[PDB]
Image (cartoon, helix red, strand yellow):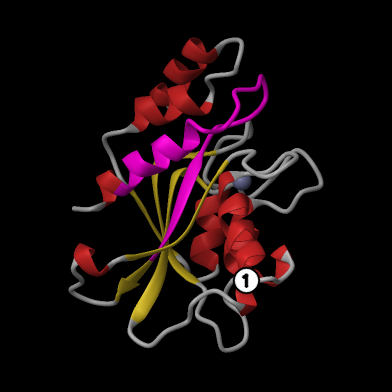
């Protein structure tokens, strides 16, 4: 019920990303939600991010977590130590596209950044919502979803925004419109 609204807010974040010929403009919002029969009024925003918000070749999930790490004065790879881990609440990430499980560079993929948050006595991110079951990379596929399931992280596709999410994501690409039509065909 609130999921489409959160993904529209994610799409507005994605539009802050600079269009480039090889990037995927994505936005992400991390939410703390009461477990069970929750009220969206009681949601708390924990962090936000978008592709290339931070210098270099950064993804939306990466920027979302690194923003929180910077505010809490820890290195980005130790953000798991400071993310909320409260009784009766769960961390939920909304992101326009499926988190990637493979990156064409040496950078850690987004699903691994998500899985990393569950360490020690910290619950980490418990569920991912996204609007297109394709990663924010050229690879395509569902490897991100498979890695989430293998790690015990829930995920759910929210239908109805696929074309708009893709049009924004690949706005900087030479063959963007033909590429959108192919992704919607998939
Ligand atoms: Zn990614």
- In terms of depth relative to the viewer, which is nearer, 27 or 149? 27
Indicate whether residue 20 is drawn in magenta: yes
On the image, the x and y values in percent for residue 126 come to 44, 70
Whether disc 1's CB lies below 8 Å from ligand 1 is answered no
Residue topped by disc 1: 72
Identity of the residue drawn at 36% across and 25% down:
163
For the C terminus, give its image quadrant: top left
Along the horizontal axis of the image, is 136 left or right of 44? right
In this picture, residue 62 sits left or right of residue 185: right
Looking at the picture, does residue 81 appear above or below residue 168? below
Image position, residue 70 (x, y; %): 66, 63
SS at mark 1 in the image: loop
Residue shown at 75% from the left, 40% from the top: 56
Relative to 87, is 108 above or below?
above
Instruction: Measuring from the top left, give residue 87's x and y in whole percent.
Output: 37, 88
Say whether residue 84 is magenta: no
Q: Residue furthest right?
A: 106
Q: Residues within 10 Å of mark 1 (few under 14, many from 20)?
A: some
Start-end of magenta stretch: 6-31
Compare residues 47 and 111 and report the one nearer the observer. Answer: 47
């Amino acid at each position: 019920s609130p999921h489409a609204k959160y993904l529209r807010e994610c799409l507005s974040l994605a539009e802050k990303s600079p269009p480039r010929p090889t990037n995927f403009r994505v936005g992400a919002i991390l939410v703390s939600r009461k477990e069970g029969d929750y009220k969206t009024e009681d949601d708390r925003i924990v962090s936000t991010g978008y592709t290339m918000e931070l210098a270099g070749n950064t993804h939306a999930e990466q920027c979302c977590l690194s923003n929180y790490a910077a505010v809490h004065s820890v290195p980005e790879d130790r953000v798991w130590e400071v993310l909320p881990s409260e009784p009766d609440r769960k961390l939920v990430m909304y992101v326009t596209m499926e988190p990637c499980g493979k990156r064409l560079s040496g950078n850690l993929p987004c699903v691994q950044r998500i899985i990393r948050t569950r360490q020690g006595d910290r619950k980490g991110i418990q569920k991912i919502y996204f609007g297109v079951k394709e990663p924010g990379t050229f690879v395509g596929g569902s490897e991100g979803c498979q890695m989430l399931t293998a790690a015990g992280i829930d995920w759910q596709v929210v239908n109805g925004l696929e074309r708009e999410i893709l049009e924004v994501a690949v706005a900087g690409h030479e063959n963007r419109e033909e590429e959108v039509k192919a992704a919607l065909d998939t």
